[PDB]
Image (tube, coloured by chain):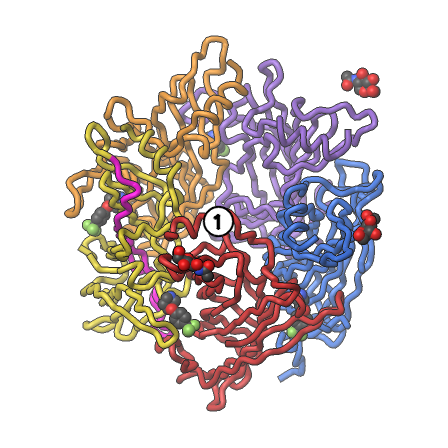
Chain colours: A blue, B purple, C orange, D yellow, E red
Amino acid sequence: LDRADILYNIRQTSRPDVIPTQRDRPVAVSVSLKFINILEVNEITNEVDVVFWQQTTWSDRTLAWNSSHSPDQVSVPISSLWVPDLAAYNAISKPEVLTPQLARVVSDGEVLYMPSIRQRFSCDVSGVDTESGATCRIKIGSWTHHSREISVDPTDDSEYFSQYSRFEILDVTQKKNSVTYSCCPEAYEDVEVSLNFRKKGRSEI
Amino acid sequence: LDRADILYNIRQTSRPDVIPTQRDRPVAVSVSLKFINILEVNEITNEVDVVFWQQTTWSDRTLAWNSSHSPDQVSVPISSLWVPDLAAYNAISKPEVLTPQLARVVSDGEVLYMPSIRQRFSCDVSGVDTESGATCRIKIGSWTHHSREISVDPTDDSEYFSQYSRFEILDVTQKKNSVTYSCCPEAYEDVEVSLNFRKKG
Amino acid sequence: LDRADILYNIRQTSRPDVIPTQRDRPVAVSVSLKFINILEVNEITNEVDVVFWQQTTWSDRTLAWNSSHSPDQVSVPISSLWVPDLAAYNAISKPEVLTPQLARVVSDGEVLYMPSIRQRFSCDVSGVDTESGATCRIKIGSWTHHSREISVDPTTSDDSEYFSQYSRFEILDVTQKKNSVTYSCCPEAYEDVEVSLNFRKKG
Amino acid sequence: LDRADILYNIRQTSRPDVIPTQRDRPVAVSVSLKFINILEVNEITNEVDVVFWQQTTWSDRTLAWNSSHSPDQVSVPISSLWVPDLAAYNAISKPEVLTPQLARVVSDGEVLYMPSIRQRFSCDVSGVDTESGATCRIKIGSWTHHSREISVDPTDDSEYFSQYSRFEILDVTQKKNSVTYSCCPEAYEDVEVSLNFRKK
Amino acid sequence: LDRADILYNIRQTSRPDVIPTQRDRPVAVSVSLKFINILEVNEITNEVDVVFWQQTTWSDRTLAWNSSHSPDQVSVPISSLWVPDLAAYNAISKPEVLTPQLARVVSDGEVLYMPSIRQRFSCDVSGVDTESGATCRIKIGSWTHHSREISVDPTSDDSEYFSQYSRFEILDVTQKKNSVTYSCCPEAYEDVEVSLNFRKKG
Ligand SMILES: FC(F)(F)c1ccc(OC2CCNCC2)cc1
Ligand SMILES: FC(F)(F)c1ccc(OC2CCNCC2)cc1
Ligand SMILES: FC(F)(F)c1ccc(OC2CCNCC2)cc1
Ligand SMILES: FC(F)(F)c1ccc(OC2CCNCC2)cc1
Ligand SMILES: *[C@@H]1O[C@H](CO)[C@@H](O)[C@H](O)[C@H]1NC(C)=O
Ligand SMILES: *[C@@H]1O[C@H](CO)[C@@H](O)[C@H](O)[C@H]1NC(C)=O
Ligand SMILES: *[C@@H]1O[C@H](CO)[C@@H](O)[C@H](O)[C@H]1NC(C)=O
């Protein structure tokens, strides 16, 4: 197969509305945020404006092809794929996608989607101007798929962080959690990302 | 049936433009706001910028399937479903939907749609910096379907509200009302949501 | 007929690009603004930010059905209908439509479309802080259809009936009058409704 | 023919990606800006926010019909027409179109497209608070078509300016410019609009 | 062939989702920024708002036609073409495209795409108010195609198209080839690093 044949097959049999569950087991979605910049912090309102790469991986076996004498991977527009309906539960702006909306599909059906996102959050900005810094927690999970349909798992903290930010990263921790909504008995899995950061140049003058 | 068959059937037959009235009774729509954040308040202009989850449920029997050896629920893009034409009558900004535009459909045709919305309102902000706080009333009902076509029913306070807001919720009440427009004799049902909130000390 | 049949017929025979003229008479479009809020006023720049319901009615006989044992009215997405190409000639922002983009269609082909719009205008804000107030004129007409294709008419109810009690401003008077403009370029006249909003800052 | 038949024919045989050149002559595009408002001026940054009607006309003979017992003109959505790929070379914001995106098509194939646009420009704002005023020059041309494919020609310009603006128009001049760049052998046309305005 | 036939052929067959690799060589993409304006600079936050022409060229032989008694070039909407998935790795805003989204296609399959973009960047603004000025580095490369699929190469006066009305002036522009690696994957991504040396006029 060549790239043209693989992309044709995906475009033609793309069920983007259909979650690719295998034998009624959940789709395992891995999520890791790589922080690139912290642009605005407001200690009065407890709001932060951040740029991050949202590394997202899952399997969709309906995409798979025989890689013998074929590409091992192709770039696919996400409009041609099912993508997990992830939301940041404490976002106060829509995610602004800064990058081309293409995912990488591996011949075994693994999908890697990593948009660069600018987004504003409600989180704890207290201590940003101190040595120990602020800890802003961001919670990401499926909006509509509970734990029997989607599982969410986490996958240098400053490796891609801008050296030119007014802020610096002290630590990033990413832990699995579970939330319940009042309407409904099912739990939703989430990743809770704790961004420990502080303002550069905190000497009193 | 599997998910692929159910979603195919819904996409092919759901009639998103067709209100799913049964035997000329109104469609019963339930609406409840869960307040998540209060972002900006202006006591001079009487404007508030709020984030809320708009829990919306109704029945559409045209979506129903036999759940024997089948999923009991599916996630469906709202572009493939009829959705009630709800509007906040005192909104001064378009609703900004922060979440994926998917609804949950149950095999009996019950639909659950709960977008996270950021929206600005004209309401009473007087007393926000006092112990008793401000009471901002938000009115939500059908833009085009009167009470013979859509009924709106409300059916805890602070449960999902951000601990990091500058504001705190003292009380939320959600009560059924009716409005009439000058053009037309028919009443439109609404839910009136009273948000009692104050600036934290 | 049921709602499903009527909406199917409209969706299938919808010519949304085709003005529904009858026997080469103009389409009579009625426009009435119901002011809901005055949000920002700048007396230096002569700019106002207003929210209004734009009550818009016209006839499209291609939509009509026999109402015997049928609904008298249905809700239709405006993407399935011809709608008049109305513009506010002194708007300085795009109209922000706050409401679901549905119209009501009556079995005789009458259409009622009433979006809630937030929009900014260039108009006379002088006198806003006085007892007699400011008079801001908003002109709304067809962008491309002259008077032989579209006529715009005010309708024949309290000016403040839907106006927010929480606005910093109050309405003293609203008048809505028919106006015609003829440009040097072109022989044809373009109709508008001129809406005069007399308002002031509350004491 | 009636309006329904003409609009059907246009929608069905619309090649909106195909420039309507006749016998390898350029498409003659006329552009005139009618200034409506000057909203924000910054003399420090040399930026202005303006509202104008962009009167745009050209011929597309593929649209033409016999006007005997037929309308002389119809309103057509611009998504059903070829439109010139005009850009304002000194714009610093996307054009905000304030009006319905319809053009008028005449039975001889003339197209009249006149959007109301709000747009921000980088131009000379120096002297805005003086008697002689500022002169802000706006250059509009085809982004991808050289002079053998599109010619741009100027066609009152101040007549419909808002009496309520903080600013007033002293003069508008609109001239043709033809530019050959070092990169490329072909000439590109533009219209250069000089807006002489001042604070009242 | 006339323009209508060429544009019909491209619209029917161009495969915009398909990278036009020849015999498993990478697609050679040339990228050069022409700076038009510097609109806002913040020395505290190290942010700049810039307008530039992103001159972008590559070959797609699936677009080619016989130019005998035919146009040598046509204008094509980029929705009908494969375009490289270029991103500015240090952008902090979406690219605002100010121009019609059309490319020029030459009869040999060369594509020339040059959008005018307004975009905000995180870069070194230190020294902007000094004689030596600031040097702001912008890195542009493929978001999803590594060096075996896309190669990036740089291709007049640095101020030739720069606005005389900017508060800033350009001292120098240099454009060099580099490579980046991401943690997920062993493969390198080629980029152009554009160094904009500029200062405040006043
Ligand atoms: F002011 C008010 F709340 F009492 C009110 C709200 C809405 C309203 O009419 C709407 C009914 C749905 N379609 C048209 C507008 C009348 C009064
Ligand atoms: F300025 C002018 F005289 F050149 C001019 C102005 C307007 C015009 O047509 C208007 C009437 C139809 N709706 C908006 C444009 C033609 C010429
Ligand atoms: F600089 C350049 F070589 F990249 C370049 C410059 C100008 C140019 O054409 C102009 C006229 C047509 N619209 C774009 C600018 C093309 C390339
Ligand atoms: F920071 C940096 F410049 F060193 C850098 C930039 C980009 C990068 O990886 C991207 C390559 C294409 N896929 C998305 C990530 C790694 C480092
Ligand atoms: C993949 O292709 C190879 C080589 O042609 C062959 O061994 C095999 O049939 C294929 N594998 C599967 C699982 O279909
Ligand atoms: C539903 O499923 C069961 C199991 O096959 C079937 O026997 C029954 O008739 C069905 N009933 C309805 C009403 O769908
Ligand atoms: C292109 O067409 C011309 C004229 O019809 C013909 O002479 C020639 O063989 C063609 N050229 C190529 C390289 O195919």
Q: Quadrant of residue C19?
A: top left
How far across and down, in percent of the image, does residue A68 sit? Answer: 78, 56
Q: Looking at numbered disc 1 in the image, what kind of residue is underneath it?
A: Arg
Circle 1 sits in a helix, a strand or a loop, which is it?
A: helix
Q: Main secondary structure of the magenta part?
A: strand
Residue B79 vertical placement versus A29 (above, below): above
Can residue E44 be seen from the camera position used here?
Answer: no
Residue shown at 52%/53% (left/top)?
A: B42
Q: Is B173 positioned to the left or the right of B74 in the image? A: left
Q: Quadrant of residue D106?
A: top left
Q: Quadrant of residue E101?
A: bottom left
Q: Which residues are magenta?
A: D36-65
List the single residue furthest toward the top: C68
How far across and down, in percent of the image, does residue C53 sit? Answer: 41, 36
How far across and down, in percent of the image, does residue B1 sit? Answer: 77, 28
Query: Which residue position holds label 1?
Result: E11
Along the line of sight, which residue is nearer the eye, C181 or A42?
Answer: C181
Q: Is D167 positioned to the left or the right of A121 in the image? A: left
Residue shown at 25%/28% (left/top)?
A: C26
> Which part of the image, by quadrant, shows the C terminus of chain D?
bottom left
Q: How many marks?
A: 1
Q: Is B183 positioned to the left or the right of D38 in the image? A: right
Along the line of sight, which residue is nearer the eye, A88 or B42?
Answer: A88
Along the line of sight, which residue is nearer the eye, C104 or B162?
Answer: C104
How crowded pointer 1 is (Cα within 10 Å; few <14, some 14-19, many 20+) is rated as some
> Which part of the image, by quadrant, shows the N terminus of chain D?
top left
